[PDB]
Length: 337
Ligand SMILES: NC1=N[C@@]2(CO1)c1cc(-c3cccnc3F)ccc1Oc1c2cc(C2=CCCOC2)nc1F
Ligand SMILES: *[C@@H]1O[C@H](CO)[C@@H](O[C@@H]2O[C@H](CO)[C@@H](O)[C@H](O)[C@H]2NC(C)=O)[C@H](O)[C@H]1NC(C)=O
Ligand SMILES: *[C@@H]1O[C@H](CO)[C@@H](O)[C@H](O)[C@H]1NC(C)=O
Image (cartoon, rainbow, N blue to C red; front, side, top):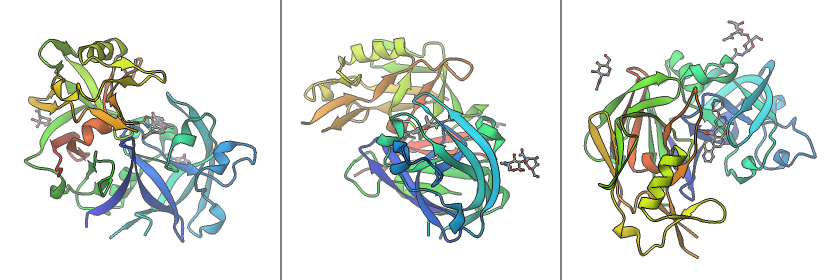
């Protein structure tokens, strides 16, 4: 009864699986993003002269018998850029072909995607798996709608993200259960503080034994739609100096690959349990073979911030369970090889 969704892994930075929209299903690749709450894919009704209109697969409402028109225009903004379009209603299949059919799901037909962001993305769109409180246009999210249709037993979903770039599979989303093959030991849970993002209280962050960040407590979100670990700019700048990383030309922080195994252990201490990240795990190897820091400084302003983002680096190292029945997040050491 729980549904397994294969995930592809692009350079440890993007994790996306296949879904279907319409009857017959039109296949789209989406990032299952716990940092938003809307489902949107590109539309055929984009414009010939926009470059985003030539990149990803497009929703064609003519070819769907289950399509019904909503038409309400939407406009979505965030850090990297923005997109806009109008809403539609159709059946959503997970996966595109064991699977389930979510009926009467309102989503977004993106007709304009300015910026250079979406050109870099190997995925067509986004399926938000956050709370309804951050859903633009107050659109009932996919997971909320599927639980209303009682399509899985448990009001939970779980993420395995393989941080081995060449390994297979790239990851696995588990709708309605948890996959014990992909984690050792037992799960330990944190209560969600703010039901908007998957927000969590963090007691402190220890970079070795000489630098303590998030001093006196701070707030964090568990976000599968963010590649790296993100914290306040000033705090992460201390972290990069403590590990000796220097900013490159593009902004990435680099550290010589010889010095990796001599770098301190970084412990995220939240909710009575401690979560270790050894230097081999919070430092990425990119191609030349150059080693980059897994941390990124970004000031998220109020009311949402300041926030730490436990992105794919953290989730790829700890199997994560998102639980809407008891509003809590679970962690367990992910199985490797
Ligand atoms: N968690 C998170 N999702 C992102 C940004 O941060 C987002 C992430 C990505 C992204 C990029 C690279 C790898 N993985 C990703 F998920 C791409 C597009 C994108 O685009 C959006 C995102 C979030 C949002 C939200 C809109 C309204 C609610 O607040 C966030 N909107 C987007 F268009
Ligand atoms: C989809 O279109 C409808 C009507 O064009 C929009 O209005 C919703 O309609 C429902 C029908 O029962 C009413 O409860 C409300 O007037 C609206 N619902 C909500 C949740 O706002 C609607 O906004 C559009 N989008 C969605 C996601 O329903
Ligand atoms: C989390 O919240 C639930 C709500 O009742 C409570 O039962 C549980 O003890 C809480 N856990 C912690 C660690 O505070």
